[PDB]
Image (cartoon, coloured by chain):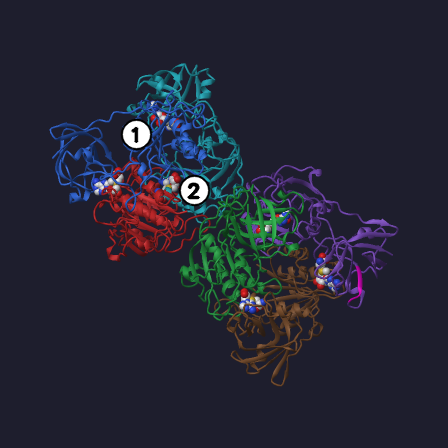
Chain colours: A purple, B brown, C green, D cyan, E red, F blue
Amino acid sequence: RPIIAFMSDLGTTDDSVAQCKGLMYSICPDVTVVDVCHSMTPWDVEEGARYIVDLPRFFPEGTVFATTTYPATGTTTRSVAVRIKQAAKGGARGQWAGSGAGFERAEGSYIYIAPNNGLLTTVLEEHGYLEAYEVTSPKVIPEQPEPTFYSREMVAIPSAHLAAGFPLSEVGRPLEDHEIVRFNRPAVEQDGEALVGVVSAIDHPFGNVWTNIHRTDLEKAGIGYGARLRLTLDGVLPFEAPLTPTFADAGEIGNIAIYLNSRGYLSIARNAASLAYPYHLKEGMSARVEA
Amino acid sequence: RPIIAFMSDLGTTDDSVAQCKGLMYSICPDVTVVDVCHSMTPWDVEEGARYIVDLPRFFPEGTVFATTTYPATGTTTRSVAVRIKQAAKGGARGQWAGSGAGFERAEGSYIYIAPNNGLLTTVLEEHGYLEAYEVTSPKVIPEQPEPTFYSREMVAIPSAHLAAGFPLSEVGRPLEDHEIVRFNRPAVEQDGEALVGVVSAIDHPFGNVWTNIHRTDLEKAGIGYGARLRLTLDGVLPFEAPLTPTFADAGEIGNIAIYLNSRGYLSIARNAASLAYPYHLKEGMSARVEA
Amino acid sequence: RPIIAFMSDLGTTDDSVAQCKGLMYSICPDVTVVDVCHSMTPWDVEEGARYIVDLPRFFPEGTVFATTTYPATGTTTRSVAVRIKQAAKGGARGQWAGSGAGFERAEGSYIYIAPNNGLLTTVLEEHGYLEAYEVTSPKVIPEQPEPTFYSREMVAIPSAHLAAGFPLSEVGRPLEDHEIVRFNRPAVEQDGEALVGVVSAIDHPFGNVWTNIHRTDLEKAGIGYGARLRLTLDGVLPFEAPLTPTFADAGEIGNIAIYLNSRGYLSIARNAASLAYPYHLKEGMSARVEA
Amino acid sequence: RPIIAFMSDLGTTDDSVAQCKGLMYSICPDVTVVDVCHSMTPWDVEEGARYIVDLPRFFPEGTVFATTTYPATGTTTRSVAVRIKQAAKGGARGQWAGSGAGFERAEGSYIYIAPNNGLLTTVLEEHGYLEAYEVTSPKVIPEQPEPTFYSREMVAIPSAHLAAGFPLSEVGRPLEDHEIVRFNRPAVEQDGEALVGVVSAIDHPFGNVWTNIHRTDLEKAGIGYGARLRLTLDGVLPFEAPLTPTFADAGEIGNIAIYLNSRGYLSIARNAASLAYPYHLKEGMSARVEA
Amino acid sequence: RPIIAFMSDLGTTDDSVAQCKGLMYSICPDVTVVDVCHSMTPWDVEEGARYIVDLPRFFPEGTVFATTTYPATGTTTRSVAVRIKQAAKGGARGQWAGSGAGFERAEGSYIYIAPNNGLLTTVLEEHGYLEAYEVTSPKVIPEQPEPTFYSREMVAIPSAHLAAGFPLSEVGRPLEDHEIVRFNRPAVEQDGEALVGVVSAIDHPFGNVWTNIHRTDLEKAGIGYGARLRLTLDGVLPFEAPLTPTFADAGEIGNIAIYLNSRGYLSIARNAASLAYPYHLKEGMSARVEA
Amino acid sequence: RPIIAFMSDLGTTDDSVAQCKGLMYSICPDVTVVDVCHSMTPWDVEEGARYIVDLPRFFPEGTVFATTTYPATGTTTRSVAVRIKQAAKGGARGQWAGSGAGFERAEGSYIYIAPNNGLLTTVLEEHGYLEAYEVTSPKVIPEQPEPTFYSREMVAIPSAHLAAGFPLSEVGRPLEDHEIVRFNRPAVEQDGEALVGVVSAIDHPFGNVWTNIHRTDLEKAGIGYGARLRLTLDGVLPFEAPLTPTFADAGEIGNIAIYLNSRGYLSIARNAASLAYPYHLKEGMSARVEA
Ligand SMILES: C[S@@+](CC[C@H](N)C(=O)[O-])C[C@H]1O[C@@H](n2cnc3c(N)ncnc32)[C@H](O)[C@@H]1O
Ligand SMILES: C[S@@+](CC[C@H](N)C(=O)[O-])C[C@H]1O[C@@H](n2cnc3c(N)ncnc32)[C@H](O)[C@@H]1O
Ligand SMILES: C[S@@+](CC[C@H](N)C(=O)[O-])C[C@H]1O[C@@H](n2cnc3c(N)ncnc32)[C@H](O)[C@@H]1O
Ligand SMILES: C[S@@+](CC[C@H](N)C(=O)[O-])C[C@H]1O[C@@H](n2cnc3c(N)ncnc32)[C@H](O)[C@@H]1O
Ligand SMILES: C[S@@+](CC[C@H](N)C(=O)[O-])C[C@H]1O[C@@H](n2cnc3c(N)ncnc32)[C@H](O)[C@@H]1O
Ligand SMILES: C[S@@+](CC[C@H](N)C(=O)[O-])C[C@H]1O[C@@H](n2cnc3c(N)ncnc32)[C@H](O)[C@@H]1O
């Protein structure tokens, strides 16, 4: 019962995703295609990365992740197919997902296929990888690929061959590590006893504010739940709350909560109200946290 | 072939829904997950209720409805799982759905799982229930549930266990009726021989206007198809038309139709034009009908 | 493994599409329902037609295409169900889709079911058809159809019966060709050797600009992939570039590309940037191209 | 433009071949079907082998060879489909076919599909193969195959699916070499400094006599063009002549030529007269050559 | 991609068939001409019938069958063109042809054109017809037809006009049923519990013996696979075998097999040896079958 | 849509013709290859000539006629390629072929390519020619031709290049008329006013008898369609009948018809019965006709 989990920049307003799906069922008749999202900002490989890096622990072993924003579509660039190493625990704690004690996932159990444009930068950093190949064989891509639709030609199509059991190492030649394109991720800076980062995302549809300050950064300023914090956004908004597990800990509806989001990152919100929307807070604003 | 029908407030802009689906396929490998919608206004339990109350008659017997907006995520609250009694006829006329005379559905054939925050208020009113349980067993929820994602931890995951055949009565202790939270439904008032309600929803993407005035409220006033109505909105924007089965009965395109929608409620529209959008008509506006 | 590909104007904000899906699973339990889109402008049959005309070559043989915008819902009109002839090659070049040399599809392999309102106009022009029938049998539609929901009653429900093996010729009487409603496609006209048409679509989410000028319009205008073009939009905005296969051929991020999109038509974009959104370009604006 | 080249034992006296072709055009609408021959002695796998071993170098790359005599039709046996390795030079000299220096053919460019009964023995010996699969998938053969017509059910039909782009590896499980049936090729023996073979074929319609003594058997005896040979047949009818390139080198019409045929093998004829017919010479007769 | 499937009595030894083909390509440049056979006994309309009655299910809808033996060539007789009703299932079981569950063929989807000499007797009996016309219009036949070649003038030529889309009903006037010439087919006689018929054909090139006793005649003496039968040929040869699906069921090579042939008729053969040839068995000999 | 019409002495019993076809498709991928016949008596150039002389008026303009019996294969001889002048009317009367008044063909529209051995003798006599060239260029034949297969090397291969647009004048040097080998046609001679010729062919499969006496030989012998004739064959067998247009004019099945065949020549047959086969009549027997 193979699964392809599909994340693209193709949108939800025309038949582009359906074209790709049609081809997935043609190649792998017993497949289940799970939509991740198709709503990302086109060409923002850093946003795309965010929607896919946390996926593996939630899916059955053998799942293929077909992930693509493809601004170099039509050129002589070719996709990269990689078998990751660690499925990786996640969340505010760092645990397996599922009921009971969670579903432990074996190593070497998921494949990602993507343009070689840095989309997989965070996947490779947080999971590692065992093997990586250029996608070139005409067994798994078109001999005459549509120039403006490499997300279909070079990702959707070969993803389905992989789901159907095409050997990974036969899609094309092995890639050396330096041949895999990466974007740089800005580090969280130690700064006195303060940690200095950015708003990484506005968490839609709620308007929560997510930062790039990870639980591990907090876990060696020595900051746990209960700590009284000052989280300054945009240089000029010094929010103050204790770090709490969840929104309702702030008390009355509308009160500020500082918490660790489900991806493991320091976040700020209001309790059952929107923080970001009324005040137009945005990705890219500064975020400093301290006692 | 189990089905879970999934309605949430998680949105369509990141991987949130997909994480849920991954676990659903993990737990119940044979399952089909049907998206109801994920676009509801967060925390608006009355809106969520409208998207789920009409579902049972459409679905195969044995379908599990996983329905969630979870503003109390991370607190000691626990989800409720209920087996409904009557699948219930619906529509403007009150009938079974499907081809021929429709598909009559047996009693006791659908389970809802939701936060215990009133989301199921109208489901329980219109369908009844046979049994209800608190969802607490670590066989069906996580031992260490993610504080900010109870929509996954306490709804998606246990829904998949129920679809996989986990006995409903084993999810946790039985609930007494007074322990299941309800919201108050605004009452249609009689004011002279006029009926006074509210705009319950704008029917996107068309811009039709739905009220909370039911066909039963109309048949108790002796108002049937053919009747000349004055229907007044927001307390100034008035309208006049006979009650007709459908939009085309208003004649020329753009003309006003007053009709019964597919959920059984008095509604107003323009024939193949939008009523609500040009005039910025809105849910919450007063709606008064006089004959 | 029956598939129904489903394109509607029902939106993504309530349970409308899920009601249809529920019944599709009720009638055809082993079906896969693939969403095309549900976001088209309500009642815009020409837009709807664009989202379905290119589908067949991407899908497995036997796929049913359930395609609906139904402004005449609740009237005496009845749907049309047709088995197309040619699956038809497509793309900027004209090819079968898939890996290798692509996947050929046998003739007569796909059925469309649609309101008889012209929605299938371009499907029948591009693919031809082998048989057509009015959809009237109570074996495949309700005896008492819901007046405002013919997209469910007269499209979704009968599509599921067809997917399940119900004989196409038993749905109702055969329709003559003149009884199948058609829309008039706006023709690409002449002044000098400059082609004058329209913007047929903004290609979301990228903001690329699609015209109704086909590859064939360009050949024997003597415009080939080398040609330096002046393209005026809305009778005001002029652009200049050679015709190229893809976006990156423009050079730097932001540069103008005039190209043939993946559906076979002359289009214009910026390279990994949005052309339409910053200039507020729209469907239905005039488009003029000259060497 | 896919080609299937079709060799069978179905004859030319009824509609058998045509039924096969009808299905081939049905499945692969763009296909060209080329008849090799349908006149072979039924069930004679060694004869069929001779009509197909020399074909690849003549055909465009990507050609599918559908080759069948099927005495085990209706049993549990299943056809084999193999992609050959080397297209292989041929003729009296050993060269590529075609104008100029010939058309060199890339490796891995031809598929044979046949009963697994030894028919492909010489194809595999002379060309090698890259992969071989059992043909079992109901995507490419009938669910209820006609018991007496496996030449259509298990060869013609799947050949058309391969020409239409169905992935070879999806026809069924891979075969190990020992699972592909072979016949034993009769060995050319050395008897003194004479070579002892057999008449392998009468070359109709001319009545030339072909032996199984190869040019490589001759060059290993230091026998080249110009050599005076005694070639003895059926163990009594002897002949004497030099080895020459062609028939006209025997001088007057009716004179004996000893030559290398276009398949690379020692042969004997009369110059523009028949050798075999007047004397009723036959395949299976002994053939001994002394220099 | 129109197809003409061509069956004649013109032979394979001169340019007669090529003349007709040349004219087919002249009239319908995109046509594919599929040879059925050209080897029938001249003027034996009953043999001709046998080569064409089984064709439709194997070919794409819209195929034109050009079928002719024309002993009345040069007279004032004119051909008949008919659109058949049922494509009809066939074979030992009675099923659609092709991979999977077969290709279902729509009604009214094939045209036959023939001399009105009884050639179409079995086509009309087993398929039925919707409309029939005399072929007279000089749009589709020569004004001055070659007297000795009506197979070209009155069949080949108009067949190509029909393939190219000439309206069937415009070739000439409608024919009443009684105006269509039929030969009589001898019935299978019930006779005790024995069924009494004839050898209808020797199945070349194998020498299998085909009778006119159909699966339906067996299917109400109550005779299925496994029944121990006595099949007496020529009054004096009481063969005995169980009815089996195929030849190899008889066991050792040479053993007698009684089976249902691919056309649906009771047949007798030897397993991978010829029955008819060594003993000179012939069409027209008696055939009786019983328990 | 290039066509090659292919007449050889290669037979229908091995892969010889398919080797030629493979290369024709290799060189001219969009070609249609039409078989004329491959069954002529090997090396009988006069028989070969009969099968090709009447072809041009039946085929689309631009058709290449590849026509070969090559007993001088492997010698220094080279083929001749000629563009004929007149397409030429034919038949018992002398007309253009096709529906209506027939299809006129422009002058200079067809090329024949043949061994320079007299095979084209009657083609050049009946049609004339505009240009002729020796076929020597390595652009169109092999540099190292297979000695025993010049029908492939020097006819099939160059025919495909000509079909593809290769300029006829670039195949080799122009040939003067005297360098084109001719055979001597046996002349219809005189004793009294009785015409004395030969049986030119047995018209298989019917067993009709063709003489070398043309319609023109008969006119100004004063023999018209009323004339009562005595025709003696082989100097022994006498027959009597009037000259009629067709076989059925003889009356009862079996009666004698003397007529003009579809190629323009005096012939004799039985009405829907074989004249030649029962009496063992053959090509080359004497034929004598008198009023
Ligand atoms: C935040 S979401 C999980 C999806 C989120 N995008 C993530 O990745 O973690 C889970 C539940 O949290 C509740 N929630 C989200 N933001 C909230 C807030 N600010 N206050 C109260 N509850 C909130 C929502 O009702 C939703 O059902
Ligand atoms: C009303 S929608 C059904 C979904 C709707 N949200 C409901 O729950 O009843 C079904 C068909 O109604 C047609 N429709 C909706 N609003 C209309 C209007 N104002 N005029 C004409 N047709 C309308 C649409 O084209 C749609 O395909
Ligand atoms: C154009 S989309 C195909 C869907 C599109 N609606 C169509 O029908 O062709 C495929 C890839 O093209 C890339 N793309 C789209 N527009 C682009 C542009 N203007 N510049 C560079 N890349 C673009 C996107 O990143 C996407 O993954
Ligand atoms: C009998 S044929 C099908 C054509 C036949 N004329 C018909 O219409 O059914 C299919 C395969 O059957 C095999 N076959 C035919 N006669 C056979 C026999 N007597 N024993 C074993 N196999 C036989 C042949 O090898 C041929 O490839
Ligand atoms: C030998 S055939 C090629 C086909 C043959 N079956 C083969 O596979 O090599 C090619 C030309 O050879 C010529 N040929 C064949 N046998 C000949 C013979 N014994 N003497 C002279 N010419 C011959 C024929 O006229 C024919 O056109
Ligand atoms: C004579 S054939 C044309 C081919 C022939 N080889 C020629 O070149 O004219 C056309 C039709 O004539 C009919 N025919 C041929 N010989 C006949 C005969 N002796 N009596 C009656 N009909 C005949 C056949 O049934 C055939 O369909």
Q: Nearer the viewer, mark 1 or mark 2?
A: 1
Ligand 5 visible in quadrant: top left
Q: Quadrant of the C terminus of chain D?
A: top left
Whether F187 is drawn above or below B94: the answer is above
Residue E130, how many percent across, how many down? 33, 57
Disc 2 packing (10 Å; few <14; some 14–19; many ≥20): many
Residue B82, how many percent across, how many down? 65, 68
**Towards the viewer: B135 or F196:** F196
Residue D113, how many percent across, how many down? 46, 38
**Towards the viewer: D4 or E264:** D4
Chain of residue at mark 2:
D
**Residue F124 shows which numbered tag?**
1
Task: Name the quadrant containing residue F12.
Answer: top left
Whether the magenta-drawn stretch holds residue D125 is answered as no
Q: Is residue A29 left or right of residue F263?
A: right
Q: Is residue A205 left or right of residue C81?
A: right
Q: Secondary structure at mark 2?
A: helix
**Residue D156 shows which numbered tag?**
2
- Residues shaded magenta: A254-258
Whether E45 is drawn above or below F65: the answer is below
**Towards the viewer: F53 or B88:** F53
* Disc 1 to disc 2, C-alpha distance: 43 Å
Q: Amino acid at mark 2?
A: Ala
Whether the magenta-drawn stretch holds residue A255 is answered as yes
**Towards the viewer: C264 or E187:** C264
